Image 1 (tube, rainbow over the protein chains, first blue to last red):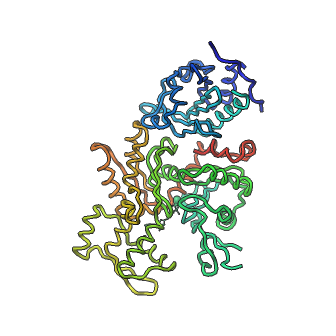
Image 2: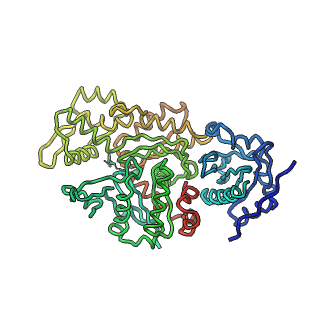
Image 3: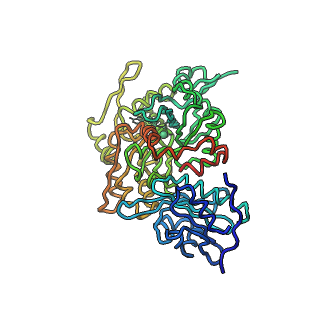
Length: 13
Length: 139
Length: 362
Ligand SMILES: Nc1ncnc2c1ncn2[C@@H]1O[C@H](COP(=O)(O)OP(=O)(O)OP(=O)(O)O)[C@@H](O)[C@H]1O
Ligand SMILES: [Ca+2]
């Protein structure tokens, strides 16, 4: 079926 | 978003040669991975070993990740607070070997393999931080 | 600048600077405080023992008294090494299987109390393997408080496979006291214990065949040695010379149910990957003061050969400098280009807290 949506990435440091 | 960005993020600093996000519930599959490397080829069977009930047999003679032979160094994958397993690949005839960490989130495994000479602690630390992030996001 | 290397043992602290070929300071891991209503460390505490209550903050290789351990560390930096710890990345050592909470506390004290700029915690047996110029092998490390068999793959200890025996040099001293007392000598007091530790270190040895050696001792006097006590009088030591370190092979001698060090070497190897076993048998390295008995390498060679498959290549490495191999391997490891990535920095501690040690140090 496929992967779920990806959550937003960590804060860029 | 999407999962490929996660691979971009993990590979950015140049310390890893391979990285993957693998969904381990139901029918496992790679959600994203470095093209043309090792983790992209991980199988449902190999995932089952990683996450399975048996935490002893993979010490008799190791496990595989996308066909690659590895030895288990530390197994805390099912332990609260750690959620990590550290491994080192095994090679034939002094070809280089590499450290690997797998961390476990609510829905994924994050896998990282270091480049030659990169210490397992750098790899573990990176993999753990990304797992922590994903868990905070309910993943 | 110069990294520090501090190897804290149950009996002895070994400290100094990375790049040096030997520890600058070696002194007893004791803290003394006044017997009655501030503190002394090491040689001074021993010298003043008559007016102090002495405590050993490390028990069987594990830190158990944190207040006294901080006194040891402060003394080591300021009095023995004469350095300001805020100026030096610091490599510490820890026992195999050191509890999570302990290595966290070590980390927290180093950064919060001593304000070191960077630090690392390495497993003692792993450093001994580096001292022998290897990164794969199995170490028997035996000190004053604890003995371990530690198999190591590419510089990584394999904790699932580590064996512990809770007897080492102090137990052997006490046992030698017991059996010399059975013989008819009186060794009971603290000062007498110190004499017996000296007899142990100078006259004991490991027999190749224990039962035969007992039959031999009984059949002539060629195995007797005399020892001159401080007061001046000279005493005789017989089968006691080899019965004492025989305890390592037969813990039942002091009423322990545990298997001997040869058996636990085998059991440790057999917990490891089939693929690395040949390398472990070919790379057995002895470490620690209690591996200094004459004959111990020969006996280990014999015993391991009997345990292993009949054609296995077995090699026992017993470096002359093995009282200090842990410290020396820390000095070697901290001097490598490959180690500079391994330090935990103050920045990393600030971001992650004490549990950074679980990510970074293994
Ligand atoms: N030549 C020798 N023969 C026997 N024992 C010795 C000899 N030299 C030192 N020892 C013993 O070695 C012990 C100390 O060694 P070591 O420094 O390795 O221990 P430690 O690090 O203090 O302790 P541990 O590792 O158990 O925590 C003492 O018990 C001492 O009596
Ligand atoms: Ca020691």
